[PDB]
Length: 73
Length: 10
Image 1 (cartoon, each protein chain N blue to C red):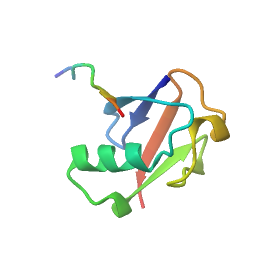
Image 2: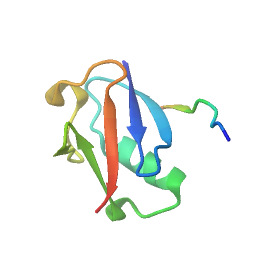
Image 3: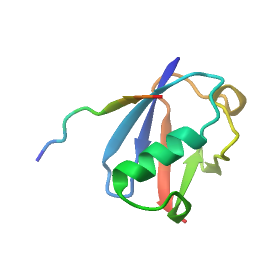
Image 4: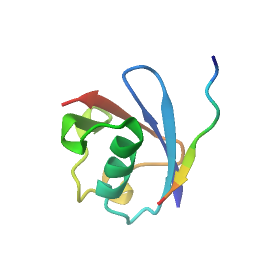
């Protein structure tokens, strides 16, 4: 497992503990739910590149405490 | 003010 920090446009953070092999759709959906907006209204970036629903932390090279940025789609 | 820490397990 690793902890990822999801940083919003307003500088707020929600952190997620996920498995290295987990498809990140679940993280996207949980974050959008907590922001009260549709998942498709947001885009989630790692090092500026879009995280797909079927990407895993392992595939993206993510490490403990790495940042995911959320932007409006 | 200052937000508390939020960690969600999936």
